Image (cartoon, coloured by chain):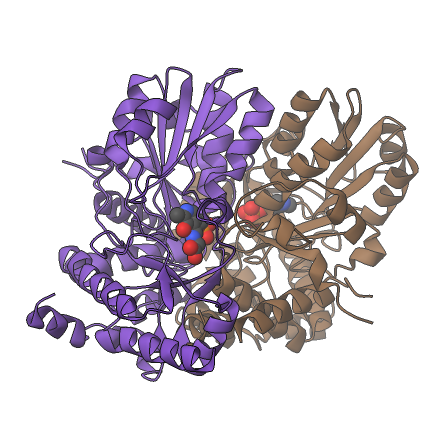
Chain colours: A purple, B brown
Amino acid sequence: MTDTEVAQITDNPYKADFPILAANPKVAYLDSAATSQRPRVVIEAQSRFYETMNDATAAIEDARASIAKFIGAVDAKPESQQIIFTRNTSEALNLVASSLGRYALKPGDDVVISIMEHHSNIIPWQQICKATGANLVYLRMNSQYQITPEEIASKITERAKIVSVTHVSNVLGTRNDIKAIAKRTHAMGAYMVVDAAQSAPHILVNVHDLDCDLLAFSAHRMCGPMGIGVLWGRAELLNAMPPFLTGGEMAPVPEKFEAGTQDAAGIYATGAAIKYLNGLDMAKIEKREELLARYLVQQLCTLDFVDIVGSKLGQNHVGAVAFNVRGVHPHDVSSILDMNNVCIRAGHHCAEPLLIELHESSTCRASVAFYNDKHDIDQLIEGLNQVWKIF
Amino acid sequence: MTDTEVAQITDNPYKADFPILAANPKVAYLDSAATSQRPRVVIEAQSRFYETMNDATAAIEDARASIAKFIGAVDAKPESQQIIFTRNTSEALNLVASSLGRYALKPGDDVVISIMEHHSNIIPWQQICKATGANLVYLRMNSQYQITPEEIASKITERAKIVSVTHVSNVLGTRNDIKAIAKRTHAMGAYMVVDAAQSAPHILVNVHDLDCDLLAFSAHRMCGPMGIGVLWGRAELLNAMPPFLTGGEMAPVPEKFEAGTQDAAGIYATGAAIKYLNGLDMAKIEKREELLARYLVQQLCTLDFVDIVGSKLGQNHVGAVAFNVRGVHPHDVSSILDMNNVCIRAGHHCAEPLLIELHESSTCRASVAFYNDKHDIDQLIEGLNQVWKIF
Ligand SMILES: Cc1ncc(COP(=O)(O)O)c(CNCC(=O)O)c1O
Ligand SMILES: Cc1ncc(COP(=O)(O)O)c(CNCC(=O)O)c1O
């Protein structure tokens, strides 16, 4: 890293835009992989909705539009009638597993997930597979923590019908080669689902580059409100899949997939959040996070009592870094770190299969967002040192 | 009605507490059966959440607690580990139909809904019935628009396994005799589901009086945020039913039924809304709404060109009054009424089976909340008269 990149990490042009951070300069918040903080604009936008609207229809679709363009889902018109609102990524994944699974799995077909999956991209597929007569096949990692072109070609075969792989691991921070896996999957007559809850808020997503069929994520990782998950699909498939939830207001896509009154004020704020990110220049966002990502792991590697659970190179870490203090249970680490005003995730991160694979029970995790600065990463370091001195 | 009851309807001690109404004295809002307006307290409470918390765990359960006590779900402790959050009433009903339906329907069992049902209490049961080998039986109405003790005993028999009936009709305004239907249903070895989305915000609900097994509703009819539906269940059944959505964070009840990150800021505001209603004195609430209910229908009956689609007695109308101007399509009525700054629902209200039963295609609907006054009901009347003069 250059001396002028530590300069960029050292300045924080963004933290003022967050009330909770603005109110707490003493706090280092290092869990954005869990949920983001909210910009003031997004908090007010949603309060606004409830206080003036409760036209509103014009604004839901402008939100659909804003999200669609943000994920590259264009035509030159944003494909807003092809994005659906759920509660969060888990629900969109449950929906895919139910609807796509009924429409597509014949008995003895193969559904393929990765060992890197979060539980929400595992259990629904297990059910789908029991209900349907289908087998669940996993893609495994190499020494350097990758899904290699050999694993892809060898585990996605002609028996494959659905392939559902995380874009970015909430534990390792690995960016998976989603377009590669897409192309072998189509070859084998199979549908590409991408869990992108942890890629969408950090790197750029373009569904038409990724050439996938279903993409899901949540809004609360990209600065949006809780309560909002989004799914996108190829129109033809959205028209073809059965509906999942049924009732009133469930018809055409998207309405076919949105039963009941929806969180309009939250869909509205989800728009404000997309509009807030594109204003920051989304490229400058991805750039800052990589400098914060690289600075953290470099710093973590000066600490010998610490084991980074993943690639020791930080060019490879998108958003999230998993680690262990040698001999200290992560719950103990997070406690002393909270006494030092630092926020890290501790445990298995609802990715237990991955952690078994790497022969771990628990890990700490630190995760970076654009509204963090070098001092944030220095607090965790100086707090981790307090930890060692005690243990 | 006494001259001192028109006095109570004439004063409005509540409208100031709503920013959207406060900002629009010219507007008469008569669609609270669709969604309520939000109190300022509830708007700020949710903004608050995002700006200070994003302990938070202490507050989700205080919300669970507040809701539980509000529906009488006590022990003397509130049964908060027995209420579950969904997105809205439709999802809770979909969940029941899936989980309870898998756990309980053997082929040739009978599931019984009412003809008064909203679609969200119909279609999931239709699916459940096709998947399971079970028959869907409907409870029908008499001349006076009731589910009589003969209909109950004759359509809920030993073949019955699930009975799911609306507590209050979003079209007729009828309060159904839920405890009666509960008691015949148990007799026949069957589970009592109550769709109470339209009863919970107006009359008192006590799950232990109603002696039911599942109750659902939404928060946005009782002044809470959109995005929040609640389900309650008898603990033993909640422990026994399969989980519906699966993934991460889905285990014990309630967590077994809440997959993924949840709308904590919205669950928080849902608490603020319950806490706002009990402060108003919930009894004084039910009382004011009946005076507004009685005044509307009495007034509507002076208008001859108008047909009230339901009981002409307004002691019987909870919350909602359906009607038609003779010869005018409701969409036309709502348009001229919107030019007169009045808000009514027009159409079939996602209760099409009911409307077929009553030989109607569309109806207008007016619905009253505690924050309405006699002038609100006088605007609709004087606007309906404009309608006739033109048609
Ligand atoms: C890769 C990935 N996929 C799906 C989900 C589920 O998202 P929802 O909560 O919105 O349903 C998560 C959550 N990741 C949780 C964490 O690492 O903190 C995830 O990291
Ligand atoms: C009796 C009843 N049950 C269930 C629902 C579905 O509720 P959700 O939107 O929260 O999912 C409704 C909605 N009633 C809509 C209306 O009359 O305007 C209802 O009136």
Q: B47 or A309, which is in the foreground? A: A309
Task: Report x, y in % for residue A22.
Answer: 30, 80
User: Residue, x 45% and y 20% (percent of image)?
Assistant: A104
Residue at 49% x, 38% y is: A122
Which residue: 32% across, 44% down? A145
Residue furthest right in the image: B187
Q: Quadrant of the C terminus of chain B?
A: top left
Above or below, B242 relative to A279? above
Which image quarter holds the N terminus of chain B?
bottom right
* Frontmost residue, A251 versus A119: A119
User: What count of labels does the image hold?
Assistant: 0
Q: Quadrant of residue B85?
A: bottom right
Please state which of residues B364 and A50 is positioned toward the viewer in this rendering: A50
Above or below residue B113? Residue B269 is below
Image coordinates of residue B9 in percent, x first then y, are 63, 70
Q: Is residue B114 visible?
A: no
Is the residue A180 above or below the residue A277 in the image? above
Residue A253 on image: x %, y %: 38, 31
Q: Which quadrant of the figure has residue B158?
A: top right
- Image spot of residue B259 (x, y percent): 54, 49
Residue B162 occupies which quadrant of the picture?
A: top right
**A315 relative to A259, above or below:** below
